[PDB]
Image: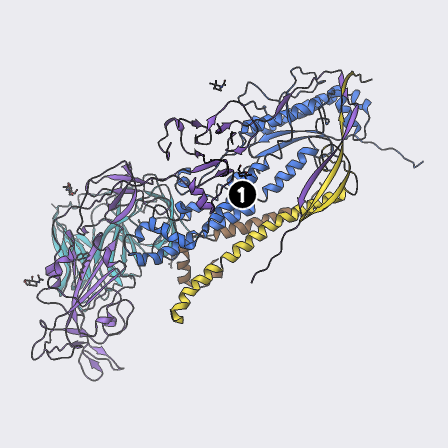
Amino acid sequence: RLDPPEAEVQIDRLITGRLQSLQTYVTQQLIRAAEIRASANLAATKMSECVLGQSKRVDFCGKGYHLMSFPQSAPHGVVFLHVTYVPAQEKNFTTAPA
Amino acid sequence: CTMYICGDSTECSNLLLQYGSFCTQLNRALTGIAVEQDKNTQEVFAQVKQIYKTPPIKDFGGFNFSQILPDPSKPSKRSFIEDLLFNKVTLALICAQKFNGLTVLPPLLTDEMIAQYTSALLAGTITSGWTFGAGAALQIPFAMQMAYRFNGIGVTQNVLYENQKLIANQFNSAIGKIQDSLSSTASALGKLQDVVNQNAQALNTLVKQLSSNFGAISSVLNDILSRLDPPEAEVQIDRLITGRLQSLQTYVTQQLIRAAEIRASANLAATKMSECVLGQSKRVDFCGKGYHLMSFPQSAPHGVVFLHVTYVPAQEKNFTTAPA
Amino acid sequence: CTMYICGDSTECSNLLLQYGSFCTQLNRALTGIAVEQDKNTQEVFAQVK
Amino acid sequence: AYTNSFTRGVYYPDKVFRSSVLHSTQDLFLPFFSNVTWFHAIHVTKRFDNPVLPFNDGVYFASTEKSNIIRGWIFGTTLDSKTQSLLIVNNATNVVIKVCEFQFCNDPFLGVYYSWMESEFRVYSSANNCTFEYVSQPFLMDLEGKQGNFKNLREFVFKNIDGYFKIYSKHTPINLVRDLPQGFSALEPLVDLPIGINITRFQTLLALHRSYLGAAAYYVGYLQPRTFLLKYNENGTITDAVDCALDP
Amino acid sequence: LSETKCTLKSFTVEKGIYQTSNFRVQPTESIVRFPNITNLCPFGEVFNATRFASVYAWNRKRISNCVADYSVLYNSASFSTFKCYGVSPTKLNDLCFTNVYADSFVIRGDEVRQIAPGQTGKIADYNYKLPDDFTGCVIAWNSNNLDSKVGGNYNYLYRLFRKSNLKPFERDISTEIYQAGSTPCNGVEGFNCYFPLQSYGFQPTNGVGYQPYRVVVLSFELLHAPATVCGPKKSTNLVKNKCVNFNFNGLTGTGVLTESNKKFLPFQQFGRDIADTTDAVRDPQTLEILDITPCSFGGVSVITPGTNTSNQVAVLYQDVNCTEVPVAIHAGSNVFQTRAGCLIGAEHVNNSYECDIPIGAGICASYQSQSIIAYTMSLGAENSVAYSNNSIAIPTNFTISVTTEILPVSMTKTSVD
Ligand SMILES: O=C(O)CCCCCC(=O)N1CCc2ccc([N+](=O)[O-])cc21
Ligand SMILES: *[C@@H]1O[C@H](CO)[C@@H](O)[C@H](O)[C@H]1NC(C)=O
Ligand SMILES: *[C@@H]1O[C@H](CO)[C@@H](O)[C@H](O)[C@H]1NC(C)=O
Ligand SMILES: *[C@@H]1O[C@H](CO)[C@@H](O)[C@H](O)[C@H]1NC(C)=O
Ligand SMILES: *[C@@H]1O[C@H](CO)[C@@H](O)[C@H](O)[C@H]1NC(C)=O
Ligand SMILES: *[C@@H]1O[C@H](CO)[C@@H](O)[C@H](O)[C@H]1NC(C)=O
């Protein structure tokens, strides 16, 4: 319905509007892709100390005293199974230093 | 959005719809930063499943903990030292912000419940040891509890058993100086106040940026509508709308960027509360300078504070050695 | 800001003010990335008294 | 013959109320710590200073006196009978403003003889073909009868934009001997006249007491484009300012 | 409740708490206030009169203290040109104007296109010039019957030669020989020496492009200072404490009016705050100062157990005291005042449970004749150790346990064109 001289004026607004919604998407993706990296670094550190050895750090590879662990795979992630030692059935006595 | 961009105008409100739902996404982004803040504080303090009680009779061998234990006389039941950290950080018009659609929400956990969580860890760290971290608490006299930690760094038991009074006096005199150190200078908590200064100095720029023309006749919607017909006013109201819709996105982007730096600090505090306060650490320079013995937590506004106890040698001498 | 956007023009310099102080914030953001860089190298090497 | 003004010369740039806020503006202001000239009129060698001076973009005028010896000004381009000029006078009975084609004298002045009375008025010789006039209501003003140190100060600002003449003014009582005091004070709008002529010069006219060739002096300074920062009280007055380009 | 389904664009909602919108109040009536004045402006002395001036020496007249009703010109006057800059013709009946002026002169027929900013010609270069930021209107009409005669009319002149160009709203009424060459004129006309002023010759039989015209220019300023000329509108009384619309010398808005303590100067009429908004004004019929404040502020939230269970909800007001609540959409006697606002539609209780829906400030709500309740969240159990100086406890058995942990690793890849 309009000649080029009039169509350009109203096509520039559309172009500048549509070029703005393609940048928020990229910015948000860039921001949100920096947390999966932190999670994947923790997973890599946890696969070398609880699966390839025994850990003395408290509450790192489970609740209790660490014995061993096994890995498994899930879609877009990983799963761990931890084995621990837990006491029970305490009793009272009398004590002396020497 | 509508109360900040347009105001009470109905022509501006009707014209806004053409741009579409552009800030329901802004609100979606802003609402995800509050649940995270609520979850941050529940991984540092809520680590004990049971609320223990401080024993009434004090028989600890010569150690005095009376300055880091709850005081019933003081309201809110806060320890003496905790009350000095609450007078050194200050939370410094709000009516102008409220008239433009800006508000502040309260946290879920009150400051009185946070002090009930740090008074159970302290009570369970003195009567059981590290046995309450995994399982059920098992009692042990304190003097025999310190021998374990001495054996854990290489020294023997008779060294501790033969110098009890001196060690107790040293601990008392060392912990009696923190009070006077903190009762003089208020600049010690310099990093807990920067977060307050920010997030508060950045909410006034939003209000100040409402008095700028973006290529229009003026910056008041009641002076463009009092002299021009709708066909002409629609041309010059779009410039203001697009200008004011741009300063609401930089704020959200910067808040999103800067809220990802507190999560790392919260994770570090959560990791440091499970290894220095619920056990003994062999990692060098993790829970202080020297050889680690034990540690105690405390609470401050928007943060946490730790106190570390270490062992340091002195008075060396020279000898002669041989491999065999 | 003024040397990159306008140049030596005085008409552009006078017209810029209408948009307000929009890049003092840019400079505030840029100046906080240099103190951090200076502090980064002092926590790795300066560990011996 | 040379003095500097530290922080003097400031006028309200708009007509709107404001309180407890800092504001920034760009206008034609008199810079800080700038050179200024001194003109004398003292009879012990007698002196009588009324030279013709330029009018570049504006003018800041100040006079300290005990007995009224400064009356008005005359503005123009060639100060002859070939162009239009402007006249502001005080003939001791009322204020007169006229825009005609005058033929001014070489040494304009007024005078008194006795007690004291107004007798002589020698400014122009003829006026023709002019289209602006205004006369204020009559008043009686004292003459002479004083001697000692200076007591009064008066300041003025002149501008010429789009055929408009604007004047700001303010008066302050002071006690001093041989200088201009220091302080802060803002000037307020006075009047706006339509004339529509090209002005590139000006001059001052005085009075003499039945004498030839008592104590008074005046200053002169020009204007330049500048940007300032102003501060307001809780009441609504300006009390301090800063120049944004004086030094780093 | 129905304001959230539209917000999230669906017919089903789930458990949680949502924000919706703020609280709004609407105006009740209107109001107008204008200065009171009776005299009518001089519409006759200005437009149609005896004789007009020449272009090179025009005229200027001042108008003040009158009421502008231009409908009185419909009977006789017929204008062929009318243009206004900086304002809209349909809005001229509701405003008040300040510093008005009028100019008048006579020019030729096809030289009326040069009366406009940014133009070139012999009339816009030596006789009459207009500024760039103009505010006013231009009017012209044909006057061939009143300024022409047989033998011509030679009483209208215009300047033909000059050294430079004029400046806006400037005048020049000087006559002096003009030297167009290298020989000084010496005051006597001759070769390369001309008289700068010429004459217009008007005859009744000339073409349509050689006939006299009359021009008038109007100039004023708007909405910046006290005014003395106002249009044909009516006044009203003063209602103070309630949300109403107002018209103060052309300014429009809504809010609440109250008595203030500020003290304006003689040459001031409006006030401003940190942002460019108006919050003070002077009544033009009483000489007093008033204040203006908005009418809406305060947030809300909705608590629901899910649309698949029931249709009941509760509403939380975050800036009210339930003791005396003046703002409430509907406001069943189930009013409970927490530390985070005011709650309507929920039942208080005494015992404690584990939090289900976090309201805030140490309170929670859950759905449980079913209804909604609001308890206080509990911290946990309670215990007490037996600390003695010669006692100890030792285990005698053990247990084996297994637990799990989940961690995301990667993401999805994408591309755009
Ligand atoms: O062509 C028409 O249909 C009528 C146009 C005339 C519009 C006059 C007008 O808009 N104003 C605004 C303020 C004012 C003061 C004095 C006079 N005056 O000349 O008396 C006129 C006006
Ligand atoms: C400026 O003032 C100083 C101060 O006495 C004077 O020496 C100097 O001559 C003045 N400037 C000029 C151009 O004379
Ligand atoms: C035109 O001028 C005559 C002169 O008296 C006057 O009678 C007449 O009313 C004027 N025109 C109008 C429309 O009033
Ligand atoms: C008209 O305005 C004047 C100006 O203050 C005022 O004194 C007078 O009362 C007003 N007239 C009426 C009827 O109120
Ligand atoms: C919805 O309500 C129905 C009726 O009790 C129930 O059977 C169903 O499990 C609920 N949930 C869904 C997803 O339908
Ligand atoms: C719950 O507490 C209120 C307030 O003290 C009390 O009046 C009420 O009796 C309590 N409910 C029961 C069942 O005791």
Q: Is residue E63 above or below residue E35?
A: below
Q: Is residue E244 left or right of residue E379?
A: left
Q: Which chain is yellow?
A: A
User: Within the image, what quadrant is residue B53 found in?
Assistant: top right
Q: Taking the image as drawn, is residue A14 in sight?
A: yes
User: Within the image, what quadrant is residue D130 found in?
Assistant: bottom left
Q: Taking the image as drawn, is residue C3 in sight?
A: no
At 72% from the left and 30% from the top, the residue drawn is B279
At 31% from the left and 59% from the top, the residue drawn is B231
At 74% from the left and 37% from the top, the residue drawn is A82
Q: Residue B277's x, y, as percent? A: 68, 30
Q: Which chain is purple?
A: E
Q: Residue B320's x, y, as percent? A: 89, 34
Question: Which SS class for mark 1?
Answer: helix
The tint of chain C in the picture is: brown
Q: Which chain is cyan?
A: D
Q: Which chain is blue?
A: B
Q: Is residue E42 above or below residue E306?
A: below
Is E279 or E237 nearer to us in this picture? E237
Q: Residue E288's x, y, as percent? A: 23, 39
Quadrant, the N terminus of chain D: bottom left
Residue type at tag 1:
Gly
The residue to which callout 1 is attached is B32
